[PDB]
Length: 320
Length: 50
Image (tube, rainbow over all chains, first blue to last red; front, top):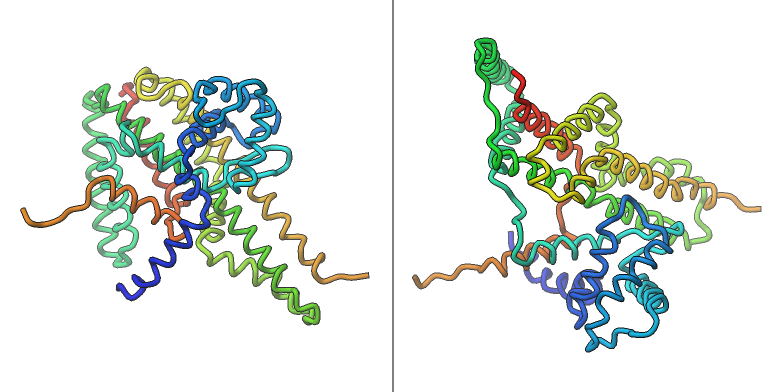
């Protein structure tokens, strides 16, 4: 379909004139600011404390003072860092939240773009095709409701695994070549890293939904009993909004203690293997080593972020 | 050859705006299942002990 094509131009004009990331990319000083921000958050576990961030930013400013054409300050690093950080918060690029600072989704996308723009390592690896093949293999074998097809698929899979077991019993096994392992490690890192990319879009979904709820209530005459069911209706509405729905299923899976613990153990043994150190620098390996911890804590943070809207029912209903 | 094709630059630029509001999402239980399965595969392959 192509009827929307007329409207898409207006949509893109909107995005250009308002969206944070795009506006950032158009600034005369875009690369310097984006690089500074990238470096700042490149070391984060979670939201960084305001003063830790201030120190790091002031130090980084010192490193780039030689770029004098941009009116970069040359006599006061802490004041400059504070001014710039305040401005960036004004740019809707980072959040005045809980004494810490987090990367707005706009910053996430701008980082992904520019960091994926120059001459670099590509977004893929030689192992991507194998992963896609396995994923399609599972997607088809599970979408197919014909039980006959499913049982036949299992009959052949079990035979393949039986071949493998017999081969190993006879004393023959196979392992990855070094560079093959390098590519697989890079593939793992590329995949798992994307899991973090959308938490703070779900956060914004909750924020916008809650602000829309409170905004529509400007009809002070509204029969307040509606919220007795709207308490469930908001949850249902966001449980079909792909953000909240997918995040809820993600939590449902994230609660499988055995699977997450096993995946962490496997990640540990993978990072231990020598090839790991070659595929990734120490920073990336440290990031991946505790990844499960990061996901757990970020999900819990987003939960306690939606928490604000949860109590809003009584704040709306009651008076006295 | 008389035809026209989009350079990689334009491909990436398109991928940028399309990753704005109308973007697709990856923080998914599906993605986690993929990563879990494929990490199992990677570990088992890297294990040399028969």
